[PDB]
Amino acid sequence: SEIVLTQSPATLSVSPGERATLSCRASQSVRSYLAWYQQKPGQAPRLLFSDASNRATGIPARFTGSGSGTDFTLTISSLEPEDFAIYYCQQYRYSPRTFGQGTKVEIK
Amino acid sequence: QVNLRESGGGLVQPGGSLRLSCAASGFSFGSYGMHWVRQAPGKGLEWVAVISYGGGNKYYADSVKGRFTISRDNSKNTLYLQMNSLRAEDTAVYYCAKDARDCLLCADWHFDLWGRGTLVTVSS
Amino acid sequence: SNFMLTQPHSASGTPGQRVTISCSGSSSNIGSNTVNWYRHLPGSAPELLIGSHNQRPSGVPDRFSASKSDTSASLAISGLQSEDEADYYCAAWDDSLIGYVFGTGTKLTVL
Amino acid sequence: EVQLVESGGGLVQPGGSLRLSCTGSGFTFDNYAMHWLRQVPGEGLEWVSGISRSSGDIDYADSVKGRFTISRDDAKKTLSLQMNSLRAEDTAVYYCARGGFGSFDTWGQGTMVTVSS
Amino acid sequence: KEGYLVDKNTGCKYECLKLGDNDYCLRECKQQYGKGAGGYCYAFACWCTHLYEQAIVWPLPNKRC
């Protein structure tokens, strides 16, 4: 039935200043209708990207979204401490709108 | 057999309010969006407001926004302009005009029917 | 002063002859969108002379010709009558601001 | 800044009902579609329900259809969710969110709803 | 002509909930663009159809949402 979103890896253990590459794969093409959200511990999700690559306001340059079709990625060039959170992708080509299970980026 | 007629015009002090009416006859009222246009003394025409054929959507001139509210009764075949927080700059003659058709946001706007006009004056 | 299309302050003519009224504008109104012509007989209802491109039912004597080149448009009145003297306006939709722009107006006088 | 504040959460038994509210500030409330989403603690996100401008278009996740009712009061700048016939698996944090034309561009801090015997 | 409905005041799209056939989009599209207009929900925005060629649709050159 509904579109399943697979996020990998499930967990990413990393140090500040490093680089993180998160992957989101859709079971079939959602073209470019893919959003990225950040959720910090004890906080609500925060929109990062829409239309897969477009940046929401106030999102730092170190964040970039890319991809199309079934494969999308979120890249953080140099992790700041505030960058440590759970990250979700979400498709809107089709109904129902669905989310990935999330990737947690946490300390080693 | 077809005309628009304005009423409700008069003299009013600043800060006060007025309601202008436009009675439509001879044509189908609800099939066409309607406009208010005004001519100030010593000046030319200025477009005031527009309302959609069904009364759902309305656009205003930046000058009148929040002060002026355009409405319509398609059952009574009349148009209404509510002028609130009136200013001396709002002194003018007001005409109700009829849009040639139903597209609100379109670049082809032209008004093929006008009324007698009513005189709204605002003095110190 | 709101933005307005620019017309001459006045135009003059002789009966049974021809007079032209000019409407000047810029891209994003004329050279983008169509131009309309109204005539306002002082004291009465303004009338639609021309629009998109031309011209009305009813008072369409011809006599009234709509011409447009790029940023400049013009209305031609032929077979002038004493009854023809009225303020004459041009109007065009401007593309930004998004809205309906009126000319400064031109008073015609028949001699 | 654009803010959303949820209320009305709490603990109820199975079969019970709750009414959640969300109040918006920092934007013209009536100019946006509004949504409810949820998150099972420790788990992912799930869209729950939504309502367009002027209440003209309304929809629900399949799992809550017939049980949940969404509404808005533009005058009060509020969004509401009537939750009936509650189930254990409805237990989750409920978020109020502003619509982003496919996405959800602003989120409240959420309110906990617990369905437990 | 066809295109996304746009709020003339804010420059932004009209959001819808039910993809495809959508009576909300339908009515808003006709009201804005006229009785002949059609409309449906595509990627959660109202997409109007059968518009007059001069109809103004999204995006507004000047105004982002």
Image: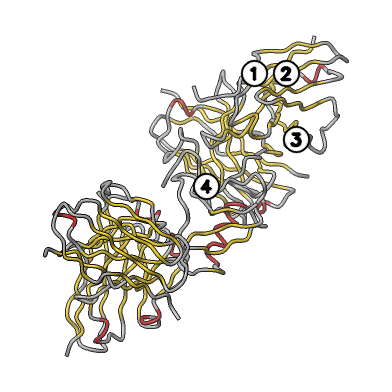
Amino acid marked by disc 4: Lys
Residue at mark 1 shares a chain with residue at mark 2: yes
Residue A6, compared with residue B84, is above or below; it is below
In the rendered image, residue B70, in percent from the top left (x then y), is placed at 52, 45
In this rendering, position of residue A9 left or right of residue D67: left
Tag shown at residue C53: 3
**Which badge, 1 or 2, comes first in the chain's sequence?**
1
Residue at mark 2 shares a chain with residue at mark 4: no
The answer to whether marks 1 and 3 mark residues whose Cβ atoms lie closer than 8 Å is no
Residue B9, compared with residue C106, is above or below; it is below
Residue count near mark 4 (Cα–Cα under 10 Å), binned few <14, some 14–19, many ≥20: some
Report the residue at 45% width, 49% height from top: E12
Rendered-image quadrant of the C terminus of chain A: bottom left
Residue at mark 1 shares a chain with residue at mark 3: yes
Helix, strand or loop at mark 1? loop
Which residue occupies the foreground of this view, B76 or D9? Answer: D9
Q: Which residue is mark 1?
A: C7
Tag shown at residue B58: 4
Label 4, label 1: how many angstroms apart (C-alpha)?
A: 30 Å
Q: Which residue is mark 2?
A: C21
Residue at mark 2 shares a chain with residue at mark 3: yes
Amino acid marked by disc 1: Gln
In the rendered image, residue C37, in percent from the top left (x then y), is placed at 71, 29
Helix, strand or loop at mark 4? strand
In the rendered image, residue B47, in percent from the top left (x then y), is placed at 56, 33
Label 2, label 4: how many angstroms apart (C-alpha)?
A: 33 Å
**Which badge, 1 or 3, comes first in the chain's sequence?**
1
